[PDB]
Length: 433
Ligand SMILES: [Ca+2]
Image (cartoon, rainbow, N blue to C red):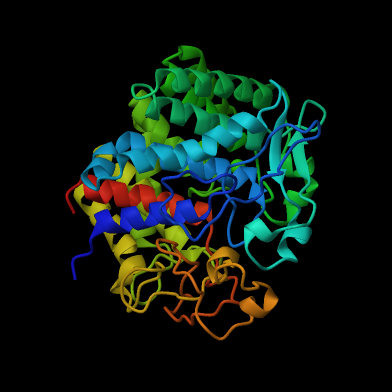
């Protein structure tokens, strides 16, 4: 009873530390993780070390990584008090910076951006510690001949959001983030195209459904970060041109629709955006399919991620003054389900009977020099290291679940899975829940 949201927030940050690629800091808290992927580089040998490994693998997928950064920064901006109350403000900022420092490296030229390091097949064929990888790690990029409005746009949004986060604590860094954000948006807007049609390897892992929502999302964030009316005008012009008011609701690495709407509602105070947001939220609370125990069931993939993302949109809607009490309560029921109100915790390393076998390579490995290979994956025992803070895919439409390492549906973990979740936790702490 009564969950310690402050500690879960700290736990989520430990999950992101566990996803760190590159050279780890002396103050790393998740110390079983070691320096890795130190040879990541671009076509000309540009340094591309750092960033976050996407999920239980070691590929650096730029699209969901950027989305993760934008949402984490977003929560830091609107619910900073939540981080401070949990004594995790510094760490919260570091989680965002780990991503943005990498995006800066990936932005090799004004209209050139590396969206991936590591190949899906070569990476996934390996099961072991990241520092033990010996396979080639190709780096793929988008440019004026191979556009990626979605990838460049989301990265611009993330950079713009981070510039706000660091505006006072590190003005120099804030300025740099913004310079890159502006250039990446121009690239995204002037060279239209889906990044997965260029970086084809990503088409079977993180294919983009549509890049138009990212353009609006990016422009909105740039307006917020610059107060430059041109970005607001562009954001709203594209919103109307693309007719986002009628797009399917929801917020996730692929679709920014609901985020764009609640964001613009705040930035413009216009009733139209608020109407769209209300309709969406009321729909979720009153009609969207739910499991018998109350969990919003939006899809079989990353089920908890979808419910937590919805919870965050609800918390953001509450801030606009929309049915604040009921929206916040419902958001809490979704987070609380993930924490254990459905019978067991679905957050590794936390609560009652949590998942102990997440589909995750680094946490499954014993410490060197012991070998870590597919026999480790095949082990009947729980993952050697507890992956504190990771939100798994979750239970099925009937609240059924079995902790299985091979189950990449229910036991999948990923950076995008914890983004909305973590920001929602910060909001709950800020609200005094
Ligand atoms: Ca999209």
